[PDB]
Amino acid sequence: ANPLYQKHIISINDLSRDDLNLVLATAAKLKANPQPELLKHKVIASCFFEASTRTRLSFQTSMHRLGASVVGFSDSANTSLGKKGETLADTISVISTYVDAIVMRHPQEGAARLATEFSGNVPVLNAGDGSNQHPTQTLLDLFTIQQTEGRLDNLHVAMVGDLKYGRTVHSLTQALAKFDGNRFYFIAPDALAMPEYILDMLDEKGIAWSLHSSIEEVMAEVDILYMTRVQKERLDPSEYANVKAQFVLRASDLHNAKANMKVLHPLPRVDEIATDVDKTPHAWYFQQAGNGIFARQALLALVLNRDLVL
Amino acid sequence: ANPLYQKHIISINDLSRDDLNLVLATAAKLKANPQPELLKHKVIASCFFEASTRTRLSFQTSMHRLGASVVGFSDSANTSLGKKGETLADTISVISTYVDAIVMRHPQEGAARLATEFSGNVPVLNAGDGSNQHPTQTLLDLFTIQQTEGRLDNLHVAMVGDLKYGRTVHSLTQALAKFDGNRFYFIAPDALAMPEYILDMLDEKGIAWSLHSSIEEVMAEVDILYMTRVQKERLDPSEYANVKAQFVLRASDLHNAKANMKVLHPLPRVDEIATDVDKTPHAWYFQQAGNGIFARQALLALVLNRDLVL
Amino acid sequence: ANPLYQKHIISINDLSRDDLNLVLATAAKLKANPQPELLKHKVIASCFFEASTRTRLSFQTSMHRLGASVVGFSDSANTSLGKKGETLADTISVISTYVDAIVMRHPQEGAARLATEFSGNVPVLNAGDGSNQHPTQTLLDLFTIQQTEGRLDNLHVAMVGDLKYGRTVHSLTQALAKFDGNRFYFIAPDALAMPEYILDMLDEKGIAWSLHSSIEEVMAEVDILYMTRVQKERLDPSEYANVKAQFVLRASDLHNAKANMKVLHPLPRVDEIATDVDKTPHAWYFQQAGNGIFARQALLALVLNRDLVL
Amino acid sequence: ANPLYQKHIISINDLSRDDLNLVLATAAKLKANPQPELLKHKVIASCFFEASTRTRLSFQTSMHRLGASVVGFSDSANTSLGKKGETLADTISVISTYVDAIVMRHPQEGAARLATEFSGNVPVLNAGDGSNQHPTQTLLDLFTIQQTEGRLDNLHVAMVGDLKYGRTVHSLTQALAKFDGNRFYFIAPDALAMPEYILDMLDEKGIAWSLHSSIEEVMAEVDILYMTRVQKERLDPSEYANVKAQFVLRASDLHNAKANMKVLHPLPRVDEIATDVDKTPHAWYFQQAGNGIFARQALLALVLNRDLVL
Amino acid sequence: GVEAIKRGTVIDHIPAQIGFKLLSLFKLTETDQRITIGLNLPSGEMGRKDLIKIENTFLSEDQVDQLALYAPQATVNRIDNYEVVGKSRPSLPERIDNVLVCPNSNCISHAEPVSSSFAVRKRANDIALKCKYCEKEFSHNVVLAN
Amino acid sequence: GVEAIKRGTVIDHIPAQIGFKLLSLFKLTETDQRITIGLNLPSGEMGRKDLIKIENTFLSEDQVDQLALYAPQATVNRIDNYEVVGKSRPSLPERIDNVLVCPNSNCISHAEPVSSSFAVRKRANDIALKCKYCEKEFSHNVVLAN
Ligand SMILES: [Zn+2]
Ligand SMILES: [Zn+2]
């Protein structure tokens, strides 16, 4: 039996360094040697209560690349869903009667772990539950860093953008904090800063981090540069715009960057990575997005197959 | 290798008489001898940014009839799509990472050819981009005329309705203008008339056309009668309604029609072809719609398979 | 009892040159001397079922400038009982039981005249009904012609823009065709050309008109340049954006203009009269907008006062 | 001609302590003696493009309490010509052709001052423009400080809540920083702390301010407790719901309060001042709300009357 | 005059009010090379012109032809040592990329990270320029009217 | 350098990659008289400079100050009959009009037929430009950038 067989995947905080490795391992095998009828005859609900089409297109593509059937919805707009008195608990109790695995994204925190209480023997994969978790994104990011950097230990990772509200930067800092010798550079306005609970955690596990004022002081040193969507609407119109310089990345800046360095972004990217960066060997956020197929595949393969032989 | 292998299909103006023939050829073979696992293991995004469910139901059915998996959306209503700062270029760059072929319909002109700049090696099939192109409709119409008329040379084709805004009549006149000896009858109000650029084109390539006042003067002569949706809202309430007679077709009218003659309509049909016509041997717009499966199939087969053996 | 007292004012077509003149005369009077209490203790309905800025605030300000009270509504979304079963007939039946006069703008042609059959002896005043009438606009357009030009006979008036669907350019021709010596230059897209009926009428009375294609083609003959709003939606984006130098006005154009020439627009505008036309002395549409008050005043004065001995 | 006659009232920043005082003096007067016909035969525009309860019904009731007539609108959805092409410039151009004064609330900062350049000599009165100004609110906040406290010099005023985005707490500081001896306690989330510029200004004039963290930290020094509305949306649910005992007020707190202390709120409220604060004698926000009328009256009296000899 | 260079390009004979337009569009100025621009120069010989001279810079082939919709009568001339080693006049190209904007307001070119391309077809009494993207043909007058 | 005109202005030691911007922004080019521009010259120190000469034109007084944010050490020479009848450097104006764009996007400037106006304060260090309409203040870095 495999350590993740039939496990619900709800939070990065729940997975171990080993669990992480095994998932990044399998992602690599499957990316190399495809398994198109692995999950023949399985049906997975893809329940996106909140619509978020890149995570969804990725997950359903992954499910199809293993042989599975997909049923589900894309609500938020609305279907006969999320309303009038039907609880999520009675909704999950019915779909688990139907399908082999529930992949679900919800507007509210804690929903996939609530899903877990009612899903019987059917595994629940969290595709984001409010501001809380999104493991599956952290997983592709880890496989992208592992594939480009050869390692998940001992790296120089800079975190740029809104680190306050970044549910992505928060899990990658906690996932990466399980391996060793990593140095973190946080580069945010003081207003959109990396939380104390994160910083406690880090200092507590003995890890080196520093706040910096410009991408610029860090560039010489960095291995991974993870950009983040600033929510323009999470600051005043005059406050976003007013910096001095800004927190946008343009190709010029990258002149001091190491040959191994990559720029990573969860996307949508709007103001923050200038399109001239795309032409650079450093830009790697589309290829990252692409690794979403293999890490996501990996997941479903390990959750649904007892002893996966590869 | 086949002449259309891995070719994007964006405009009729881009295809040749030969390319046309090859696609109409294969449509015929596949309609006769089905190939249900031809495209096993391929995933096609079906991206309908603008919703248009008959072209879409046709295309996804076609993809399923060849063995493929489909992922995608039906926006316009909306999903997490088409907004807030994500460009079509960053959207196409991510889905091409996922899928084997992009079928896409967009509200704006030029979008599928823009898609082409960012889709890497993944082929892009245009399912309509504003008032500009819709090749795949022209293709089923050509296979319908070829199947009912035995030929694509030397025909009497009348074009009825709004020929001003008809993106369908405009491509069928340019597609048909590649074969020879065809005579065109345009029957529109002077207000919803066939454009000069079209007429230039025709006169320039040496082709006979004439404006006529009633379906009625043409009926004796015609081979194909292609009806068109008048946009009731593209004229004044009193202007649509006021003609003298009208531009609606009823079974009575067809009494002088040739045995080979067919009535073709891209659908939705609302005011313009009276339901008594449906009972006639001439009515052929549902069967046309049906040929949408084979011509569309044909396309994906030639774009995705190197040397198709049939 | 003046010749307009307790009369309904629905169509320009139902008013004589004689009535038109008594309206302009009165306007002029009220304009010279404010009578703040003429309509004291009258209550007037503003019923805008279709809602609208200058005509609504113009009439309500007129009612106040004369002493009357206003009760009312605006709509297109909802507000009160009327969409199903509350027929305009039933709504007028009950409102003519409450107020001394009804001014109404409604989306459907014929609405104020239908209103006339349910308002008992409460007059109704057409603030626009569909694409049909807007007699009130016309009265201020003629007061601005009479006021800048000194007469309404023997003028060179150009109509530019949508001369086809334009409700105002139709009525304005109707009215000017009741005074002698007027020549009419029509500069529209031929796609948006003046209807035949208006030209047939004009041919009857031996009035001289002519089609034109550049405003520059007549910008040396004209005393009035009536400028109308084209609406994007009707024409194709590539259709509208074409046409050499378009039918817009820029100050440069005004360089060979007669001194006495005035540029009028019924308002709103969007690109058609450039901002530079504005600080020229020919610019007269915000003035015309202002003249809406006294013209409007004049009508409520005459309909609601037995004789105005002003 | 009093020092505010036919003046525009756009920013607190453009008014002197001298003007501020003449406004408060007049308010007081009108409050003691109603002059129901001061503005007889004036017509005033209420233009709320952003729509709003107390400031709208407060000003319209002021206009009525003084004799004037109101014409107008409210919006955020639609109602009348303005969204495309009808520029605020063009709308003010035409409305200043109709009324004697414009009071306008608009969503975009700078709107009333832009209005000022298109209203000829019709004054405009800022009812709020974006996150910028709301000088009218401020005038009633100072009349309620002067009226409960007897002065506007040498006060201990606390600002609580969102001191960062709060349009009103900014102007109120601006104004109070024009009278001598005022000490300012600032009790906000540091996340929502008072901007630097306001503190830099305050440092210039040698005015004493200080950051604080419990209302209980100063609830024994203070004469005015200005309470502002936090808006949920800006902060994370778990962020806002945290912070020990929050920045809300409960009557218990008022137990060591000076007798003369008054709790003020610009209104609306939702959780921040508990209902129990209400029957305490310190509660003064519905009163302040009421004072909106006379302060509002005062301004329309002064802008529209050559000298008020009241 | 604006004349004596030992090497470079000299766009002579530019119609007046266009040289600035040319430096703007074709981005002649972003360089740290000596450029001498002369605007509204005497030019009685040909009315009133503009003149641009860039030292140690040679505009090749494609570039001179891109000037054709703007200054169709201008004279490029190269200089390799202190004298006029060649002459060139703009020929109307098959395509014009990067510089013009599409008249079509629903064309995707309008918000995407892409350069415009128009194909040139001198037809009858003007040039028609069909857009890459929307495939709509417009007279250069409309395209240039902007 | 380049030499003599008579009765015209000559603005010397523009930075380099700035002289064109001044030609664009300040619309100096839309003239009938001979303008000559030297870009990437030397003739007066600090290595790099563009130079602009507009004959029979004089940039009277607050027009020279409007150059200060871009060429603060520029020298503006009033020339008459081949000699410098006066020389002034730019000084910081109280207000910069027409050429800047308000950094704040909920500002009304962006949609209306109004010209920008920024009041100016602090000198040869940070300079805060405050908007006429939205009244927000910004560092000149921010305003003179995106
Ligand atoms: Zn285009
Ligand atoms: Zn601003």
Image (cartoon, coloured by chain):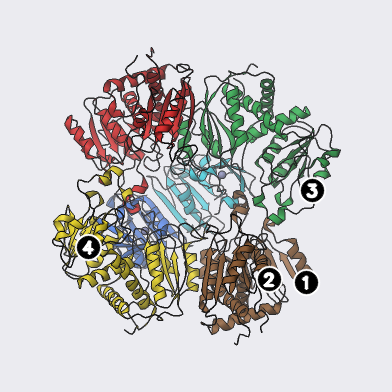
Chain colours: A brown, B yellow, C red, D green, E blue, F cyan
The kind of residue tagged 1 is: Lys
Q: Position of residue B65 (x, y in %)?
A: 39, 76
> Residue B173: which quarter of the image?
bottom left
**Where does the C terminus of chain C fall, quadrant-wise?**
top left
> Residue A293: which quarter of the image?
bottom right
Q: Is residue A138 left or right of residue A209?
A: left
Q: Secondary structure at mark 1?
A: loop
The kind of residue tagged 2 is: Ile
Q: Secondary structure at mark 4?
A: loop
Disc 2 vs disc 1: which is toward the camera?
2
State whether discs 2 and 4 lie on one chain. Answer: no
Check whether the beta carbons of the residues at disc 3 and disc 4 lie within 8 A of each other: no
Q: Is residue C90 above or below residue D36?
A: below
Residue behind mark 3:
D213
Q: Nearer the viewer, residue E57 or C204?
A: C204
Mark 1: give few (<14), some (14-19) or many (20+) Cα within 10 Å. few
Q: How far apart are the two marked residues, 3 and 4, measured between alpha carbons?
A: 85 Å
Q: How far apart are the two marked residues, 1 and 3, measured between alpha carbons?
A: 31 Å
* Badge 1: chain ID: A
Mark 4: give few (<14), some (14-19) or many (20+) Cα within 10 Å. few
* Residue B280 circle label: 4
Count of marks, rendered view: 4
Disc 2 vs disc 4: which is toward the camera?
4
Q: Which badge, 2 or 1, comes first in the chain's sequence?
A: 2
* Residue C61 circle label: none
Residue behind mark 1:
A205
Q: Position of residue B19 (x, y in %)?
A: 28, 75
Residue behind mark 2:
A12
Q: Nearer the viewer, residue D136 or C96?
A: C96
Q: Residue at x 57, y 57 (%)?
A: F46
Q: Is residue C161 above or below residue C14?
A: below
